[PDB]
Amino acid sequence: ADYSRAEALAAWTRLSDEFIGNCYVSVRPRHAPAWEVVVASAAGSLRLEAFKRAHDHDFLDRLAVAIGNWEQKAQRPDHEIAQMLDQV
Amino acid sequence: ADYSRAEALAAWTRLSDEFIGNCYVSVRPRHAPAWEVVVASAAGSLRLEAFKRAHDHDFLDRLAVAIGNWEQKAQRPDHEIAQMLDQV
Image (cartoon, rainbow over all chains, first blue to last red; front, side):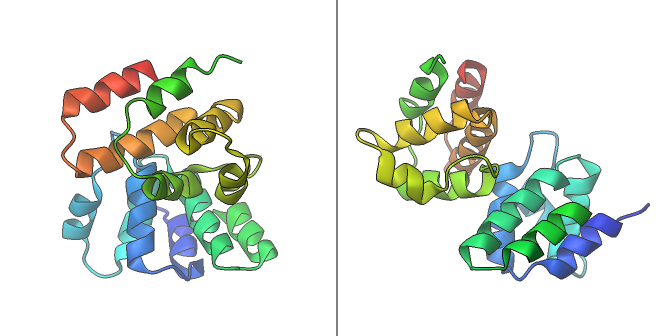
């Protein structure tokens, strides 16, 4: 079970759990568990659990874009967003 | 360009402009205008402008899923969300 990309996004982001959860709610496809399910299942890092579930359900690409969009609104440097997107 | 799906979504959602904008921020691909550009360009309905731009840039499907997900949290009936998804 290789969660390298999920772990990388978990480390890279500077967003709050509130904002990460809001992104998850928006981008979640129906075959992925709802946010409340994720939160309940989470032992330890919540953003790691969310990003693992996005990886498992093939939407981490979209979740990474959402996270990068909210980081852009908080003036995260463009090249740092592009570095994250390349990796994740 | 056929904007019927954009109009359908604009005539369906019960979310506020601010909530729609937050979904848009998450789902927007890089080649779509930022939310503030949309806001500045809308001559009529802001939500319709946003949905037309999503149609143009091939993300209206994702925006519709995001809005449906937030409506589902507001206890919008499940068949209504599915009607919107079927149409849009």
